[PDB]
Image 1 (cartoon, rainbow, N blue to C red):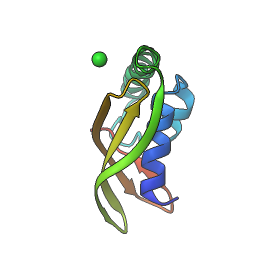
Image 2 (image 1 turned 90 degrees about the horizontal axis):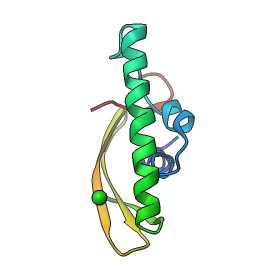
Image 3 (image 1 turned 90 degrees about the vertical axis):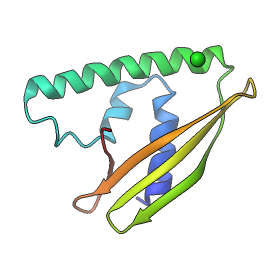
Length: 108
Ligand SMILES: [Cl-]
């Protein structure tokens, strides 16, 4: 409901192996055909499988933190840092937008 917390929960779910959870965060407005939606879903299915295998390899996620942020009333770019229990960390940007009364992650 605030974009910082949506960025962090999205990221938690991205490393959790649960594709339906991850999908619920995503704005599918760019994908303007059923076949495009499927394509996006198939890629998210794959990303979720891969991040779950990787979290396991790295001893699981230790913490999730926000490093840089740029937020206004309807858009957000948020660098989310994932810290793993093997002491390695990884970061990347989550882009979000509030089109109606709901923040959603944008497909970059
Ligand atoms: Cl790796």
